[PDB]
Each structure stands twice: as structure tokens, then as C-alpha cells.
Length: 101
Image 1 (cartoon, rainbow, N blue to C red):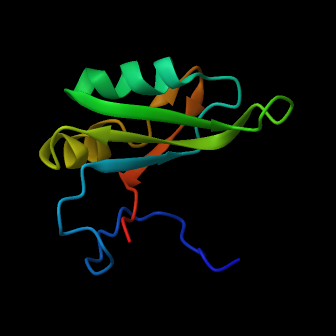
Image 2 (cartoon, rainbow, N blue to C red; image 1 turned 90 degrees about the vertical axis):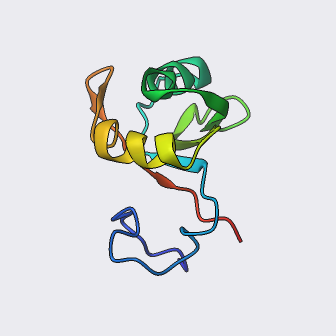
């Protein structure tokens, strides 16, 4: 596809991640996890503005990613260094600023 990005959290700078990136894309979410789980785990970092879990309408279940907007770009980064690579339900997830643009 076009979004050929393994999510190095745009550590190499660049990209749309220096504006006000509070939106955190969390990929590799456990295939049976929930928004509330995705949301609570990031609520561990701090205040989560809004957290979504991406699934099919029915069958597809968790499609393996979600988006947790923080109230801060501070706790967003905080989630990337802390929560990115977290064992959620034995699964390892990857959090990064969900590229806004």
C-alpha cells in the first residue's frame, strides 16, 4: 500500500508529528482487545481524551490497531516510550502519533 510505515514513531523526525500530535495510533493491538482496554492502558499513562479500537463491523474483530487521542502531546510521547511495546493481553502493541493530515 501507500502507508508503508512500520511505525518508528517518526523518531527520525519529519512527518506530521511536531504540530500538536495528541492523537496516538496504536497498532498491533490484541486481536480480541477492546476500546476500553486500549483506552485504559493509555489511561495508565495519563488522561486519554478519546480512544478508539478498530475492528470490522462484526466478523473481523480488532483489525489490529486503534487510535487514542491524549489530552497532551506530552503524554502521547509518554505512551510511546512507555506503552509502545506493551504486553496487552500477551500481545505487543505499538503506539505512535497517528499522523494528522
